[PDB]
Image (cartoon, rainbow over the protein chains, first blue to last red):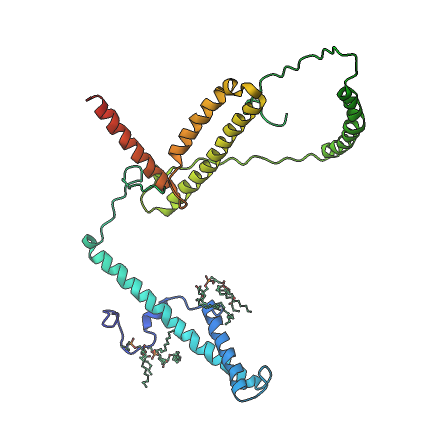
Length: 120
Length: 174
């Protein structure tokens, strides 16, 4: 649905306006999980090739972790941008059409009549 | 004293004076003199020893008091922050009212045992109160269900009040 957005630069991974958003922290829980996935891929690499799982290829295990965290950082950066855009469009559209989104009239519970169904 | 005497009333005790007629001795009287010397006094010595220790390092605990908060009738629909405090206050009062019915029931049971074979007459003030509170408790909290809440309590009251004002209105037209 968010394809022909008015504020848009097509075929860009991270448009310019995304730089005005806070970056994901290097201690982001999502980023730690992505790194943990890289480590799991390293162990499975040893297992399928009948190498010692925990020790063999520490250099290889290091690049599995780094590549996942490197790719994960940018995907998270774009994930938070696309959700910022959705809210930005949602709020702008609400201002442009106030009649469609009126301020609800609030009545206390002392006056609103709710039926009572006894449990007997 | 331990408990407030007003909350748990007890009419004054009247112990009739002994008046022996037989020449034999009363075995209980001598046992009472042997129980109070080999049981009561030794137990009192230990307690007095224990009581002295407590007085050396007295420390207090207080009865938590809850500030009043707006009731469910003063909360806007779907206002969780205002509905949260109102609902929690209602739950506390429900617990308090449960114990009130326990205080009254405890008094009613005590009267039946204290008055003995004449309980069916001397226990008239308690039974009147017991029926008084139980009727009030039933109206406030009954048939609400396991998932009871302040909203359902408010709805039940509004059901009773409407059926009362309608009854009062149409009584004059009889």
